[PDB]
Length: 267
Image (cartoon, rainbow, N blue to C red; front, side, top):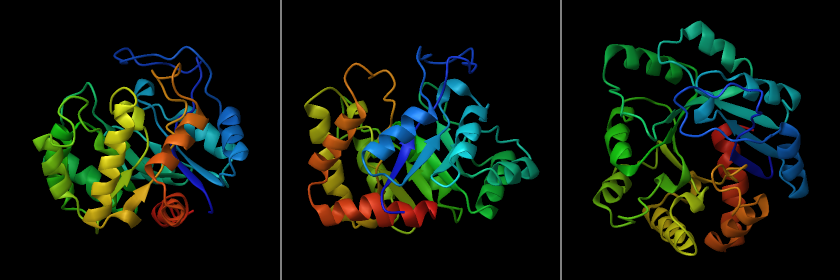
């Protein structure tokens, strides 16, 4: 559990891309290729996350985990009406949380009884809840999630608005809602924050803020390989490189790459 990449996706063109997909990549993103990047950089572990365009069919990810059960865990996407038993079954296959990827979608109501039931189940399973969502959505979600004992994990610096930036009131509210006892932030995907070299500075500011708020041990990193819709501009090496720019101090790199994700994912 020395060195952990907590955000990548595998998929193939053989996999079914759902009818309403925002996009549909036209290439192979194999476990093989992914484990190959981990090896090339001394990463001991990685976390596969279910992609938006693959809906609630978690099979590609499930198969990849099984091949490298000692190095990989997963975050699934499921209907909130999935039964406890089914969830227990995913848990048995190395799935350790579920993801609310709400880009291009409506903000669901989490208070409703059916949502509460799902969520109480996730809580029981010691699973985490991962969010990928705009600050205007996060400001809405955290308050509801405050009511459960699970870890809440926020994707890609909390997806700071490309335009409104750090001072975006929604981002400011989001920051204030963070609780050191529950929330974790991924310092991945700086390149989804805008174009270069701006987006790295945004990433750097967000990081500093996290630091001052007291959240250093709540921070984890991900390559966000294979960098969908950014393939021309971003390699694994580019991901690694920006991280070291954002997180210059190597003691902090150790916490972020090693202790923090070890503790969260219990690798």
